[PDB]
Length: 144
Image 1 (cartoon, rainbow, N blue to C red):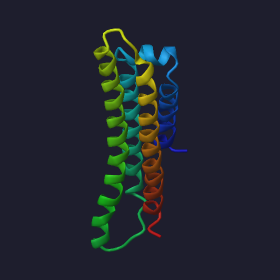
Image 2: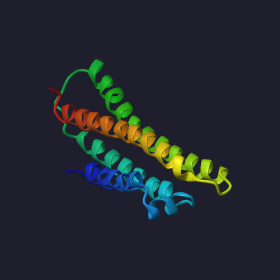
Image 3: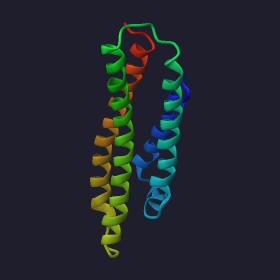
Image 4: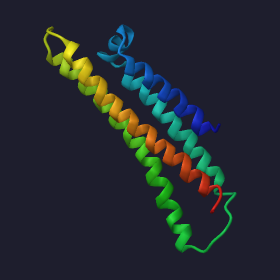
C-alpha cells in the first residue's frame, strides 16, 4: 500500500462522502470547502505518487532506449489522466455551487440528482484510470 495508494485512498474516500449529498456535504458544497479540501487531497496523492515513480527509476531491469523513451509516455499520461479527472471533478462541484447560486432560492432538489449521476459517472472514470495507473507502475517496476 504505497504512499501513492493511501493518499488517493483518502481522496476517493472523501469523494464518496460528497457523493452522498447529505446536509453537511451540500453545506461544504456551496461555499469553498469540498473542492478545496478535495484539491489538497488530489495534490498530496499526486506528490506521493510522483514520489514513488521517482524511486522506481533506481530499480529498472534493463533494455535499450526505444523503450527507455516509451517508459515516459505510458506512465506520465496515465498519471496525468488520474490528475485531470480529479481536477475536472472539482469542475463539476464548482459548477454546482453556481447552478444553485443561479437558483435564487428556488431548489436544488432536481439538481442534486443531476449532480449525483454525473458525479457517479465521473468517479467511475477516476477509478478506471487509477486502476490503469496501478497497472503501469507495476510492469514499470517489472519490465515483463
